[PDB]
Length: 111
Image (cartoon, rainbow, N blue to C red; front, side, top):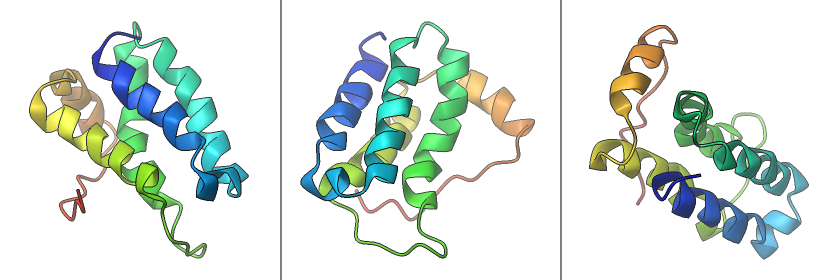
């Protein structure tokens, strides 16, 4: 991955090692699998997709499966949204792909 996805990715790895994520194999595994999805950031359009699923994914796990969220399990998705708003991501593409997806935009960011 480039720099943009680097810290978000690196943050993913750093997070996946979150002691309250280690316990949550589903949370770490997703950060893991997702982590690998960042490597190929060259496919920013492909990372844009997982990027569209990230900003809401790490928080989408709630629903019928309530939990806590260990720091590194909120800053990533948020970072993902900050990267977007900050102009780290080519949200122009995400913008086109998000249209075809009709996704969310989590305006409740808990930083």
